[PDB]
Amino acid sequence: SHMKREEAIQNFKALLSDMVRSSDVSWSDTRRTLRKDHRWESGSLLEREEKEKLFNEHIEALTKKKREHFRQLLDETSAITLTSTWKEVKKIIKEDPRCIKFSSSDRKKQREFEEYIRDKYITAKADFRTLLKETKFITYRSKKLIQESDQHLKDVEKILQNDKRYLVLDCVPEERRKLIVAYVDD
Ligand code: NI
């Protein structure tokens, strides 16, 4: 009968999968309402602690899934730029279930948006450093050259100007220039 406890876990898990679709809900509320469902007794072998554990894992799973689909939706919205605001973006994606079902909380959507943009920014810098390492007009002597005059940095920016990786940073001009400077230093 050892498998009976394992069977109860899977039963309780199926109950959660069926009845809890939102990551916003509390265990307190959920254990209240699920108790009204006759399927609840099928978890009798499970102590409240392990039920609550299973609930937490479930919320964790929903959270991960929703975040991934949210980010996919953002990745699919081509109007988004490094400088886009949640306020602007919300207007575009408002009807998409991946936005709607992410959470009832605007704060949590906004926060996930700002985190997405941060990651997007981080990824773009990494790619840009790759491009920089590819460019052999940029040498140990570049730093000499940069301190002597405006020219070298302009010459560099000319060579880089048409590359996909340089251009995705158009929204953060000062930042990009710093990256070039940083690479010229090291
Ligand atoms: Ni047995």
Image: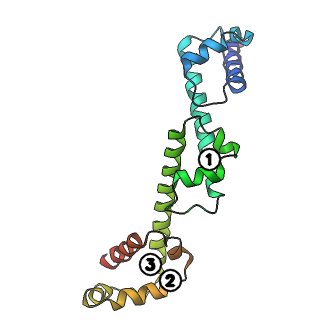
Mark 3 beta carbon near ligand 1 (under 8 Å): no
Tag 3: amino acid:
Lys
Tag 1: amino acid:
Phe
Q: Earlier in the sequence, mark 3 or mark 2?
A: 3
**Which residue is labeled 1 in the image?**
70
Q: Residue at x 55, y 83 (%)?
A: 162
Q: Residue at x 61, y 12 (%)?
A: 32
Is residue 102 positioned above or below 48 on the image? below
The crowding category of the residue bearing disc 3, from other C-alpha atoms within 10 Å (few below 14, some 14 to 19, many at least 20), is few
How many labels were placed on the picture? 3
Work out whether residue 115 or residue 138 is closer to the camera in this orientation and state it: 115
What is the CA distance from the residue labelled 3 to the residue labelled 1?
33 Å
**Which residue is labeled 3 in the image?**
133
The crowding category of the residue bearing disc 2, from other C-alpha atoms within 10 Å (few below 14, some 14 to 19, many at least 20), is some
Is residue 13 positioned above or below 2 on the image? below
Which of pointers 3 and 1 indicates the residue nearer the eye?
1
What is the CA distance from the residue labelled 1 to the residue labelled 2?
32 Å
Is 37 left, or right, of 31 in this rendering?
right
Res 148 label:
none
**Which residue is labeled 2 in the image?**
161
Is 109 left, or right, of 146 in this rendering?
right
